[PDB]
Amino acid sequence: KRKRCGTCEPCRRLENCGACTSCTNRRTHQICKLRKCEVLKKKV
DNA sequence: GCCAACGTTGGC
DNA sequence: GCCAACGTTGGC
Ligand SMILES: [Zn+2]
Ligand SMILES: [Zn+2]
Image (cartoon, rainbow, N blue to C red):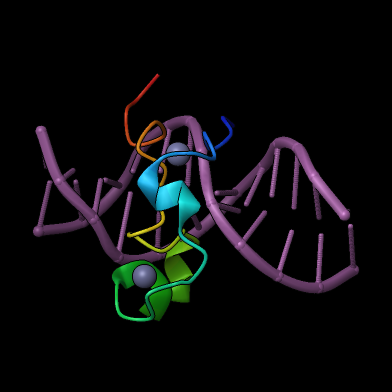
């Protein structure tokens, strides 16, 4: 697993949105879509 | 042991 | 080609 960059706009966000697939569907095991690190959205 | 969330992949 | 679902790690 890679680590989030910590400094992109999504990484800086503190709150989960509550409304995306991640936030409403905890079965996904994903971070809030608005918080997903821009670096991690690119495949290795 | 809990909890958050990354990597993979099957289903579309 | 995308992404929801699952298995898994890794910080604590
Ligand atoms: Zn969200
Ligand atoms: Zn980031």
